[PDB]
Figure 1 (cartoon, rainbow over the protein chains, first blue to last red):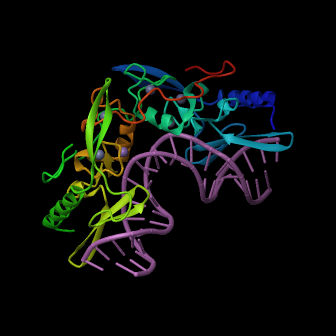
Figure 2 (cartoon, protein in one colour):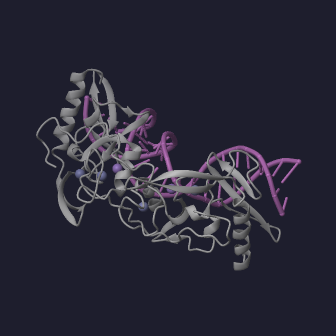
Figure 3 (cartoon, rainbow over the protein chains, first blue to last red):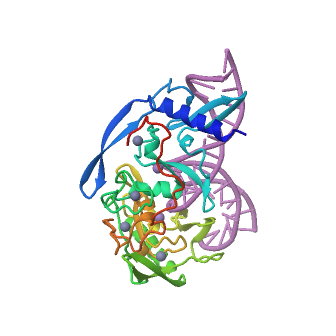
Length: 162
Length: 162
DNA sequence: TTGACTCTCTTAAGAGAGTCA
DNA sequence: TTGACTCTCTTAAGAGAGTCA
Ligand SMILES: [Mn+2]
Ligand SMILES: [Mn+2]
Ligand SMILES: [Zn+2]
Ligand SMILES: [Zn+2]
Ligand SMILES: [Zn+2]
Ligand SMILES: [Zn+2]
């Protein structure tokens, strides 16, 4: 279907449009008790969102372009990765927010990886706290920490050993 | 059922029955290059599973008892925690496998925590690799590691900063 | 060709409830 | 009363596709 040049043109038009989104400065934990700064390019909360963009769910958007009379549509965060393999180890690749900010469309805050890898970043200690992700996290995951477990392992009798 | 005595009786009969499940030894990564040994009490693969137990899904089971002529039914791993709050910070409490082995019903391998805390243990470095869970992990999570990211953050133009 | 809506689906950690014998 | 099946649902990280003007 679309040629390499046409895909590059889609990525370029997407970058042009997203680059004009409001840029919001966020101070974030990096791990190791350190703080850093991320600059998120945030899609608006309500229409209009930007040329080519439309909302398909509370925090889901799509990008649409019509080329040679054919309508093409992509998930709004998948566009930076259109020239990349779309699966790995038999798993579908997903857009994965390193900034953990769904509305952000900054491609410097996205990577392309399995849904399991994606989810796991939520609990990462961060780039200054022990992150071992080969594509390094930009921040400590929002869910990192001791947790809030209500009850631990326990038995009433003597039927079990750990 | 309603009474504390009736609940303790349910827990005691559940422990009785699960204590007769086959005990399967699993050697597991602890983090830090170390290995440990867990003893899982595994529900059978096919019926009959044990008095009071029935399968509602490939890896889902329910425990049922008749009290005051009424049938009471619970998810099979929730029974140890019937006297605990069923929510925390407005999030539902879930049975959470510290051994990451669904068929296991050893209550010494279970805790009671939000679904987010539950999920996050999949990526924990483990009790000898830096686990910070207040209710400590029994093993390194099965998904801990560098990941298999296909593409990292990137831009074609000069519109974005980290 | 374009915008602004609509709908349902995937995954892998977890759930509740009904039908028969 | 107990057993062995059936079905759909929840959550929070992610998706594809239809309708109308
Ligand atoms: Mn993510
Ligand atoms: Mn779990
Ligand atoms: Zn961002
Ligand atoms: Zn990381
Ligand atoms: Zn176990
Ligand atoms: Zn842990």
